[PDB]
Length: 161
Ligand SMILES: [Ca+2]
Image 1 (cartoon, rainbow, N blue to C red):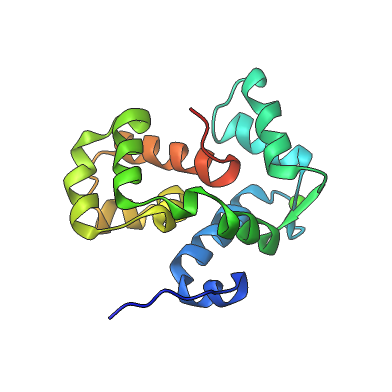
Image 2: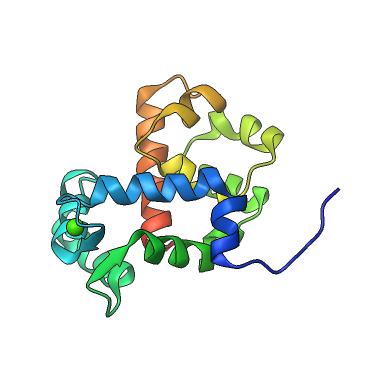
């Protein structure tokens, strides 16, 4: 029922439609002037305001997000996410993260049953809150908020800990 095949980022936009659309929603949320690209002022601004990140936490992440690219398009963001090690996380690795970093043991049995993996992280991180609420059944607003922000951090800037 399942086979392992080499796919391109473009092909995966179609196959992982909900993940791509999540990445696109995140990008629109960060793209404050709607230019279609995220600049260094927008990305740090987003960290500062929407992710409530202190100055000392931002510069490392700015560099990871941008590199030498001063203007991150949706395609750029999708490509970086598509290529990321975190997208490859197993269900096991994802549960390890929920326990050790996010501290949300209450959602673990749902995550395990649904067999979701690293590919779900953008949907966790999406400013459209319907997936965490309705699909995973996370009733707590506080819990959703915390998973969303931790997922954003990992989707946008990679895992570090
Ligand atoms: Ca912009």
